[PDB]
Amino acid sequence: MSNNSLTYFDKHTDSVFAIGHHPNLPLVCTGGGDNLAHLWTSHSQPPKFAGTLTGYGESVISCSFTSEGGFLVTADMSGKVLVHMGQKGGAQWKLASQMQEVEEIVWLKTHPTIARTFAFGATDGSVWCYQINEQDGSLEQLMSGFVHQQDCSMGEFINTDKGENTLELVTCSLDSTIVAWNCFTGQQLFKITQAEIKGLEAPWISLSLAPETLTKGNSGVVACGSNNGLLAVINCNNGGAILHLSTVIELKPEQDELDASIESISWSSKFSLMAIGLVCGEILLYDTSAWRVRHKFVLEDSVTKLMFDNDDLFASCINGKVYQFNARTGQEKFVCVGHNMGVLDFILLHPVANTGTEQKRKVITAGDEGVSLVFEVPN
Amino acid sequence: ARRPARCYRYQKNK
Image (cartoon, rainbow over all chains, first blue to last red; front, side, top):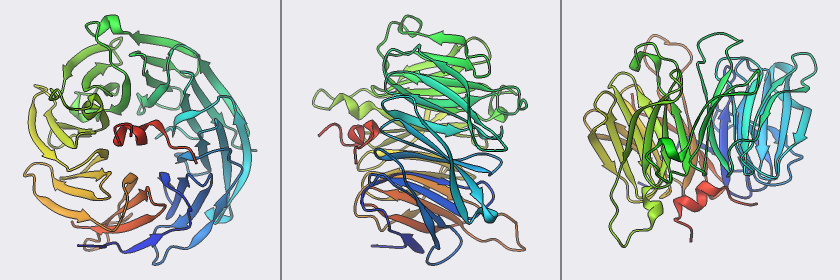
């Protein structure tokens, strides 16, 4: 009822905005409004406090390990990107390189499958993709594109199962544009504008790549959500062809328009569902063939992040809770409680090996009060 | 110490 966490980490002295986890080591990085990133372990109670990264000029808003596990990439709201090289089996993380090419970074992601690669987008609309040198960790710019005319709100890599030379990225902007890039050449593969979405204003803020098994082999289907309730599902391998476009909620006159804002999108291959989470608290589960709502949840305040995992849909909320629903039946299986302010981000950890009988997944949060909580969740 | 734009959306821009 009050705090059902397993353990906690509370060294930040301001809101925790971002949380990331090493691909193979039991290592968390969190980034905060105290302009610091902290490194700590995910497999012990209490966590081991590994250490602290410094050098930021503002709040840390991304903490991303590279897919092969050699590097950690962090970004802040003053436009800095720092790259740290793992040392001593991952116990220490040493500054290798950094840059400050923009006024403010909105998002940064490492590539999920291609080593030593990341991209970021900025408030001036610009899009950047870099690699990290394997020998000295130096920054290698692949592209820098200035096409979006307002904040580049989000990016998502596509075609990630095609090898190390297929490096493609979709980005979106508050100016209603969506662009796909070949990151190695910097070329714009396609651009969706307002004129191609029925003339509608759609300040995009969320992107999520579909699982290939849901799309008959297509590794470039992306769902896009705007801050005014527009949902677009696009085929990035057919020039951005629109597979679906709809307004997902009709607000009452009294409601702030931001109530329709689509903050997070997640796909389930098993259930052929796509879930979207709104500022008004609605979580809408769409069938991915007919693009109709099949089920919905209603939280008492804004959704901050959604994540399908097996049968479950996990949903963090600005009321400080993380909900665990059975996606098909709707059962509230668990509620992670303990935060006294909102949950701003979270990660989900699986036991690495199927032992001989089943250990629990962990939800690890980033809290607005400066705390991360570790929860063991059912299944 | 600044807060990213999504935080202001969660709060509907207090």
